[PDB]
Amino acid sequence: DKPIYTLQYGNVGFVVNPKTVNQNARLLMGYEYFTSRTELVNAG
Amino acid sequence: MALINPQFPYAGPVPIPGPAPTETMPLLNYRVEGRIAGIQQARQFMPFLQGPHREVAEQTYYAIGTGIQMGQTFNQPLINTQEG
Protein backbone atom coordinates (compact mmCIF):
# COMPACT_ATOMS: atom_id res chain seq x y z
CA ASP A 1 0.00 0.00 0.00
CA LYS A 2 2.91 2.35 0.78
CA PRO A 3 6.19 1.25 -0.83
CA ILE A 4 9.53 1.99 0.79
CA TYR A 5 11.18 4.74 -1.24
CA THR A 6 14.11 6.85 -0.06
CA LEU A 7 16.47 9.21 -1.86
CA GLN A 8 19.61 8.56 0.22
CA TYR A 9 21.13 5.12 0.72
CA GLY A 10 20.30 3.34 3.95
CA ASN A 11 17.65 5.89 4.90
CA VAL A 12 15.31 2.95 5.64
CA GLY A 13 16.67 -0.35 6.96
CA PHE A 14 15.48 -3.81 7.96
CA VAL A 15 16.42 -4.84 11.50
CA VAL A 16 16.73 -8.27 13.08
CA ASN A 17 17.67 -8.58 16.76
CA PRO A 18 18.69 -12.23 17.22
CA LYS A 19 18.56 -14.03 20.54
CA THR A 20 20.79 -17.01 19.68
CA VAL A 21 23.35 -17.05 16.86
CA ASN A 22 25.12 -20.26 15.89
CA GLN A 23 28.27 -20.62 13.81
CA ASN A 24 28.10 -19.74 10.09
CA ALA A 25 24.73 -18.04 10.56
CA ARG A 26 23.51 -15.73 7.83
CA LEU A 27 20.39 -13.82 6.79
CA LEU A 28 19.06 -14.39 3.27
CA MET A 29 17.04 -11.42 2.05
CA GLY A 30 14.69 -11.27 -0.90
CA TYR A 31 13.26 -8.09 -2.39
CA GLU A 32 10.64 -7.17 -4.92
CA TYR A 33 10.61 -3.59 -6.13
CA PHE A 34 9.91 -1.14 -8.92
CA THR A 35 12.89 0.46 -10.61
CA SER A 36 12.64 3.14 -13.26
CA ARG A 37 14.01 3.86 -16.71
CA THR A 38 15.52 7.27 -17.25
CA GLU A 39 14.45 8.78 -20.60
CA LEU A 40 10.77 7.68 -20.72
CA VAL A 41 9.48 5.76 -23.75
CA ASN A 42 8.44 9.03 -25.44
CA ALA A 43 5.67 7.56 -27.68
CA GLY A 44 8.24 6.27 -30.17
CA MET B 1 3.33 -0.17 -42.56
CA ALA B 2 4.89 -1.43 -39.34
CA LEU B 3 4.07 0.05 -35.96
CA ILE B 4 6.91 1.67 -34.04
CA ASN B 5 7.68 -0.06 -30.76
CA PRO B 6 8.13 2.77 -28.22
CA GLN B 7 9.65 0.53 -25.56
CA PHE B 8 12.27 -1.03 -27.87
CA PRO B 9 12.83 1.23 -30.88
CA TYR B 10 15.68 0.86 -33.34
CA ALA B 11 17.65 3.18 -35.58
CA GLY B 12 18.47 3.19 -39.28
CA PRO B 13 20.90 0.82 -40.98
CA VAL B 14 24.57 0.92 -40.00
CA PRO B 15 27.41 0.26 -42.49
CA ILE B 16 28.31 -3.39 -43.03
CA PRO B 17 31.04 -5.10 -45.14
CA GLY B 18 30.55 -4.65 -48.86
CA PRO B 19 30.87 -6.75 -52.03
CA ALA B 20 33.97 -5.12 -53.67
CA PRO B 21 32.25 -2.29 -55.57
CA THR B 22 33.61 -2.81 -59.10
CA GLU B 23 32.49 -6.44 -59.09
CA THR B 24 28.84 -5.31 -59.05
CA MET B 25 29.43 -3.15 -62.15
CA PRO B 26 29.23 -4.94 -65.53
CA LEU B 27 30.96 -4.35 -68.84
CA LEU B 28 28.83 -3.08 -71.74
CA ASN B 29 29.29 -6.12 -74.01
CA TYR B 30 30.70 -4.85 -77.32
CA ARG B 31 28.81 -6.12 -80.43
CA VAL B 32 30.75 -6.79 -83.66
CA GLU B 33 29.14 -6.61 -87.11
CA GLY B 34 27.42 -9.67 -88.53
CA ARG B 35 26.05 -11.14 -91.71
CA ILE B 36 23.40 -13.63 -92.75
CA ALA B 37 25.83 -15.83 -94.62
CA GLY B 38 25.66 -17.24 -98.12
CA ILE B 39 23.96 -16.36 -101.39
CA GLN B 40 20.28 -17.27 -101.08
CA GLN B 41 18.50 -19.28 -103.75
CA ALA B 42 15.49 -17.66 -105.37
CA ARG B 43 13.05 -20.58 -105.21
CA GLN B 44 12.55 -23.86 -103.36
CA PHE B 45 11.44 -27.28 -104.61
CA MET B 46 8.48 -27.46 -102.27
CA PRO B 47 7.01 -30.78 -101.04
CA PHE B 48 3.42 -29.51 -101.36
CA LEU B 49 1.68 -27.59 -104.11
CA GLN B 50 0.89 -23.96 -103.34
CA GLY B 51 -2.48 -23.76 -105.08
CA PRO B 52 -6.09 -24.56 -104.22
CA HIS B 53 -7.72 -27.97 -104.41
CA ARG B 54 -11.29 -29.12 -104.97
CA GLU B 55 -13.40 -30.91 -102.38
CA VAL B 56 -15.78 -32.67 -104.78
CA ALA B 57 -15.47 -33.79 -108.39
CA GLU B 58 -17.97 -32.52 -110.95
CA GLN B 59 -18.97 -34.47 -114.04
CA THR B 60 -17.90 -32.77 -117.27
CA TYR B 61 -19.55 -33.23 -120.66
CA TYR B 62 -18.81 -32.79 -124.33
CA ALA B 63 -21.37 -32.51 -127.11
CA ILE B 64 -21.72 -35.21 -129.76
CA GLY B 65 -23.82 -35.46 -132.90
CA THR B 66 -26.18 -38.20 -133.97
CA GLY B 67 -25.95 -39.02 -137.66
CA ILE B 68 -27.80 -38.63 -140.93
CA GLN B 69 -31.50 -39.09 -140.21
CA MET B 70 -33.20 -41.45 -142.65
CA GLY B 71 -36.78 -42.03 -143.74
CA GLN B 72 -38.98 -44.90 -142.65
CA THR B 73 -41.55 -47.38 -143.91
CA PHE B 74 -44.54 -46.72 -141.66
CA ASN B 75 -47.41 -49.12 -141.21
CA GLN B 76 -50.20 -47.02 -142.53
CA PRO B 77 -53.76 -46.88 -141.16
CA LEU B 78 -56.95 -47.90 -142.90
CA ILE B 79 -59.34 -45.49 -144.60
CA ASN B 80 -62.06 -43.95 -142.41
CA THR B 81 -65.06 -45.26 -144.35
CA GLN B 82 -67.28 -44.83 -141.25
CA GLU B 83 -65.56 -47.74 -139.43
CA GLY B 84 -63.22 -46.15 -136.90
Image (tube, coloured by chain):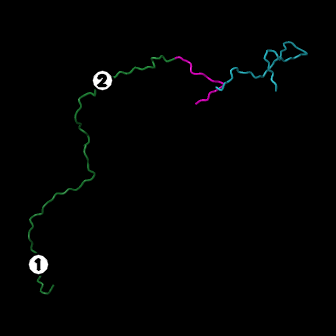
Chain colours: A cyan, B green
Label 2: chain? B
Image quarter hosting the N terminus of chain B: top right
For mark 2, give the secondary structure.
loop
**Residue that sits furthest to the front in the current view:** A42
Q: Which residues are magenta?
A: B1-17
| Residue for badge 2 | B33
Rendering coords of residue B66 (x, y %): 12, 63
Q: Amino acid at mark 2?
A: Glu
**2 or 1: mark nearer the eye:** 2
Task: Give me the residue at 49% from left, 18% from top.
Answer: B19
Dominant secondary-structure state across the stretch colored magenta: loop
**A33 sits left or right of B51 in the view:** right
Placement of A28 over or under B55, stated as above or below: above
**B21 sits left or right of B4 in the view:** left
The numbered mark, 2 or 1, whose residue comes first in the sequence reads 2
Task: Give me the residue at 60% from left, 21% from top.
Answer: B11
Mark 2 to mark 1: distance in Å?
105 Å
Rendering coords of residue B77 (x, y %): 12, 80
Residue B22 colored in magenta in the image: no
How crowded pointer 2 is (Cα within 10 Å; few <14, some 14-19, many 20+) is rated as few
Residue situated in front as seen by the camera: B1 or B43: B1
Return the mark for residue B76: 1
Residue situated in front as seen by the camera: B9 or B23: B9
How crowded pointer 1 is (Cα within 10 Å; few <14, some 14-19, many 20+) is rated as few
Return the mark for residue A27: none
Q: Amino acid at mark 1?
A: Gln
Task: Give me the residue at 8% from left, 68% from top.
Answer: B70
Placement of B64 over or under B28, stated as above or below: below
Rendering coords of residue A41 (x, y %): 67, 24
